[PDB]
Amino acid sequence: STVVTTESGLKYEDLTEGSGAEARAGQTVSVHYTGWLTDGQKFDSSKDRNDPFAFVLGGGMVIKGWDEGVQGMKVGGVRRLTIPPQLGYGAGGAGGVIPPNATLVFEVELLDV
Amino acid sequence: STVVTTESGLKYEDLTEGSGAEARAGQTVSVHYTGWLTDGQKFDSSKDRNDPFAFVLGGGMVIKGWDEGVQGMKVGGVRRLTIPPQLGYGAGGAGGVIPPNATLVFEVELLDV
Ligand SMILES: C=CC[C@@H]1/C=C(\C)C[C@H](C)C[C@H](OC)[C@H]2O[C@@](O)(C(=O)C(=O)N3CCCC[C@H]3C(=O)O[C@H](/C(C)=C/[C@@H]3CC[C@@H](O)[C@H](OC)C3)[C@H](C)[C@@H](O)CC1=O)[C@H](C)C[C@@H]2OC
Ligand SMILES: C=CC[C@@H]1/C=C(\C)C[C@H](C)C[C@H](OC)[C@H]2O[C@@](O)(C(=O)C(=O)N3CCCC[C@H]3C(=O)O[C@H](/C(C)=C/[C@@H]3CC[C@@H](O)[C@H](OC)C3)[C@H](C)[C@@H](O)CC1=O)[C@H](C)C[C@@H]2OC
Ligand SMILES: [Ca+2]
Ligand SMILES: [Ca+2]
Image (tube, rainbow over the protein chains, first blue to last red):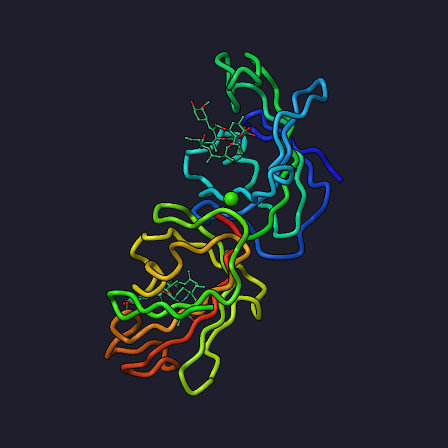
């Protein structure tokens, strides 16, 4: 599989190509995800909480790297997103668990569109 | 299991009580469903299309019997809704497949909240 670096500095890699319907901005999508810091510390997993995550793709409610990175996935696909801090939580960080200026690694599995 | 007739004339029956989180108005929920006319003709199944259905519970986008009937389900639950036409498609019917003045029977399985 390839690593694509977009104009924003986002990087993504389709670990598994989906065979089902394509995700586009406007759709309400459902995913499983895991999130890690670059040192390999896991900060979240929806699979561990047994709770698929739904959001409006392109809705401006999730971090920029997600609204961008999830577009183009197909249902069944697993995509790895490497999100620079300016497309994540920036200088501010989050919840005392994501530090300032953190690059974030997510693996995202698309369950439904 | 019991059959509850609500103030609106909706009837519902929890065929299977869910063990997980409760559905409330405001949440984006995901369900599988099958829909039948009272004569036993199936008009739709999201399971047959392999496509869970997401909607905003209480969002005024689905027929009245759904916005009402899905509230109170728990994740894992299967509820049967018997929807009189005034809480469904009324005198107008739908898609040439649901006739005028049709009572509708849905079985709804809650997958996520
Ligand atoms: C309002 C009540 C809580 C409400 C919570 C939910 C619906 C439950 C939902 C599963 C979130 C998780 O709850 C277990 C948990 O997910 C993380 O662990 C995580 O993996 C993460 O990073 N995710 C979640 C998956 C999508 C990407 C990213 C996100 O974009 O999340 C969004 C996020 C935090 C955006 C910030 C918002 C503030 C801005 O200032 C900032 O702009 C820089 C961007 C989340 C979805 C918000 O839209 C909505 C909420 O927050 C966060 C590390 C902390 C977060 O808990 C808060
Ligand atoms: C806009 C583009 C299409 C858009 C379609 C989708 C998102 C795909 C989604 C799976 C719908 C199904 O597509 C395969 C299909 O589901 C049925 O088969 C069905 O089982 C049904 O009855 N459902 C769907 C499940 C929730 C309850 C009910 C409904 O409330 O559905 C809603 C409905 C029709 C409401 C009418 C709207 C008009 C009002 O005038 C009327 O007020 C009386 C109420 C649907 C979800 C609308 O909100 C959105 C849409 O329609 C209909 C028999 C026909 C419908 O296809 C159209
Ligand atoms: Ca969920
Ligand atoms: Ca769907």
